Figure 1 (cartoon, helix red, strand yellow):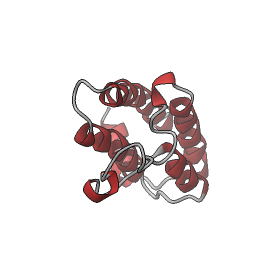
Figure 2 (tube, one colour):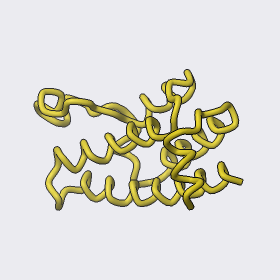
Figure 3 (cartoon, one colour):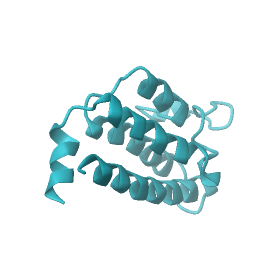
Figure 4 (tube, helix red, strand yellow):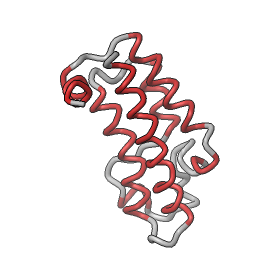
Length: 122
């Protein structure tokens, strides 16, 4: 739908939009494959992670940004979420369980994002 693509880039996020954003975020936090994205990466679990990952992101950070109305456009919310999956596939090998979690959860996020964009255009 051209309406969905247009609202994503141009339409400012409203208080009603943020209700949908929190629900999308809550669905990801409850997903079983989201365990390694719930909190910031522990440096003791990943050596030199913060020396190699330029812009880290996690679901807890996005929850704080959603609560404080950080995002003005849906593109910015999507960009932060994409960092989570891109950073994971950048740092971990393709056969790693972390890599698999990113592929599963991003596909789940894409399904939920499409539903949010659809109800936003109704």
